[PDB]
Length: 58
Ligand code: NA
Image (cartoon, rainbow, N blue to C red; front, side, top):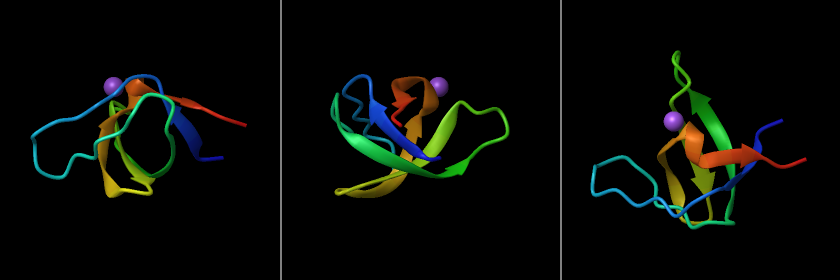
């Protein structure tokens, strides 16, 4: 399973991050060893977001 929803709006100016809106669904494509960031896919493309800003959806 790799479906999640954003807990909060997240928007960074940092290159290679993805902006997400609270309530938006996303899928996780890649993780990191420490689990703090993950590469997400939404209708707006792909990029990295903080893992603590998302939560799974069955
Ligand atoms: Na995090």
